[PDB]
Image (cartoon, rainbow, N blue to C red; front, side, top):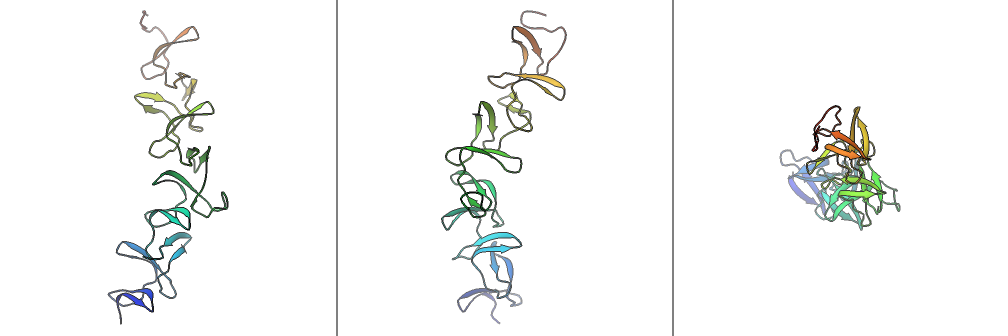
Length: 229
């Protein structure tokens, strides 16, 4: 009985060393994944559906693909387990959104698509897309509203966030940087409409002086300001 790697009638079978049996199913050999047909034990190529997970096995090396790949002039992304991944991900040229099937221009499932000048919200994560179809970073003003997008994930931010030692508050539902007076947990705060930062110390508003503590909360009673009590 032949064992080990064998090329039989031009097809790539794999009979294991120990017991010479043909190997069938998803098989991991030398840290590389293959798919051997469960009926004929032949190594297959192309697009493969295994327990509703899609893989793509190269025509030449038969090994499962990882990372970012171009197939038939369309772009796809596969995780470490070679599974076709859907969603927003980092690729060699930036950040792209790989969308479900028949989402845009009858795209294939898991294919990269064109998506410009709009927000996308995938499983409660917001992104904004520019003309280049990436997804944007840092501080942006969109429709007169301030947003922050994480420089490492392009996800829109939320909750109290300390940036350059200055606190900002982003609405938990819409992620807009809060402006003006806001009540949070029954505590009042004031954010400057021009910069968004919280108010610390005495800050006169509309010809009326108000005091905010070190942390930013608003205190009552007698307090020291530069002129006096």
